[PDB]
Structure formats: structure tokens, C-alpha cells
Length: 349
Ligand SMILES: O=C(O)c1ccnc(-c2cn[nH]n2)c1
Ligand code: NI
Ligand SMILES: [Zn+2]
Image (cartoon, rainbow, N blue to C red; front, top):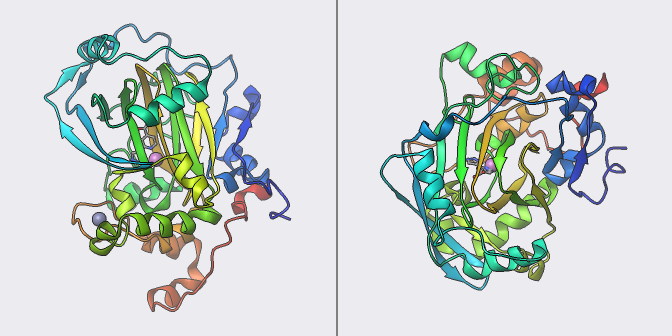
């Protein structure tokens, strides 16, 4: 039944009405009832009626406390990205650098051309990314899909322990320029993410279906045996770039999609994704959860080589939503096998 929905595991695109848009978790359950999650990634175009902010005309004074310069080393589709933190910088300061001749977007016809230039010039002329900036650009009154307060069960982490995890249960802003990249990865604890492109040039995405996620990991371990030896989940470092041609060459299924300003992207549990920004832009994102995520959370394979990595206690989720398995899980005997095709329980409504 779930297997017969989106059997291609293709990236789907949704155009909700304004009435459908009002209840966030309900629409996530809906697009899962249509098999969107099998792709790992889905686009959701909100009604023209909607806007999270009246104008972006005041933000040139907003500070980017830790701009990152992205050095990239590699060849023939395989790359490792190193981060060089620059000194703090305002948005107007950043836009100036980004729109300057040295860093601006090259001219091109179709997207496949800009794509080709991206993978051709990835290692040259290191751009700067205004990444992981704590904040939101939603006006305080917007209630539909407000990244600052989605009200999903991920809120249970803060409710129970008081713990905030920047960018995970709090929002991050991302100021991009041409050729700034996000490496191949899943979310922390294999959560969902929501990404909103407030303004600027597009952001292109690659996705690998969760049901093929393990195939991508085997390939990545093969190409980076050193990194694999020293960490059980090195892709969570978010340093590893792999071109779509390399994926084709080794039979990994994937899809691609380009995100325009004013569009949402949803990534799903264990959905590997990567991509790049076309030019100057601004994006807001955070993580969230559904009842389906819990099993993913229990089984997420985490980065083993840093003490500073994101680790969420699953205990309170298992107690509340899987009480009959708590004794078993806590005794390490819960061998529930995940079916990636199944939609989340809430989609019964
Ligand atoms: O750089 C982005 O726009 C982006 C896109 C997709 N994922 C992330 C990200 C950063 N940490 N977890 N996920 C960042
Ligand atoms: Ni992500
Ligand atoms: Zn690690």
C-alpha cells in the first residue's frame, strides 16, 4: 500500500491551499500519505496569500558573528570541504563581498550549465558562507509554518530537560553567495528539517532516498576509508561532497531539485541531501519531529569522534509513545526493523 505510493521515490512538489497550510503537522502527515518521504526531500510552495515578513529592508545591519570561508580540496567528483572562520561581519558587508565581481554568479543559459560550472569550479576561489546565524526573520505574529515555533513533539526535548540545541530546536539563518555548499548528510538524530528561502538567488538540492541511504554510506566509506576508520558516522561532519556523476557511476539513486525564494523544503528522517547556493540569498531552517521519527532517533548512528556532537536522549520519547517497548529497549533487546516506505501514524486523520 505504502510501497505502491511514489514507487519512484521521486522528489514531489506541493501546492497547499491556505486552509491546508494552517496546520503544519497535518500537512506533513498528508504529504507522507502521498509518499513524499520516500524521496527524502520535498518542496512545498506556500499560497501567494502568505508571507512571513512584510519587508527585508532593515537587515543590512544584522551581524553574522562567524562567517565561514569554504576551502574545497579534491578531484573527479570527490571532495572534502574545510571551514575557515572569518571575523564577524554585517549583512551589508556580506552582500558587498557576495555581489562583487570576484564572487558573483557567472552568466549561463539553462540550470544544467550553472550546475556544470559548480562542479567544475568547486575547488577554486573559496566563497564565504554566512552560516549558522542564530535568529529568525518571521514576524512575531505569523502562525502558519513558523520555524521559530512549529509545535511538534521535538518540543518535548526542551519541555523535559530545558536543553536548547542551536539550529535543532532553535532557528538558524543562512546567508549564501555563489558556490557556497552544504555537504552530504542527514539531520542530527536523523530528524526532519524545514528550510525556507526568504530571499535571493536559488538554492539547488540533491537527495538520496532513505531506502537507499545505506548504499550511499557504503560508497562513502569506500572512497574515504581513513575517515571511516576514525569515525562511525563521518558524514555527520558535513565536509564530504560527492558529484551526481559519481553517484550515477556507482548506481546510487538520487534526485535533484532547485529551491526558489519563498519556497519551503522538507527533509525526512535518514534522507541524505547536499547542494549549493546560486548567489546572494538568505535561508531559515530548523529540525522537527513526527511520531515516525522516534524509531529513527532510537537507531541513529552518531558521530563517535567528537564529544561536542548533538545527542538527544530518546528515553522520554520511548516512555511516552512506545511504553510497551521501554523495558525491552532499555534492555537493548528491541530489534524493531524500520520500513522506510511507511507514512507517520498521524496520517490516519
Ligand atoms: O546550507 C544550507 O542551506 C543547508 C541546507 C541543508 N542542510 C543544512 C544543515 C546544516 N546542519 N544540518 N543541516 C544547511
Ligand atoms: Ni540538512
Ligand atoms: Zn565524528
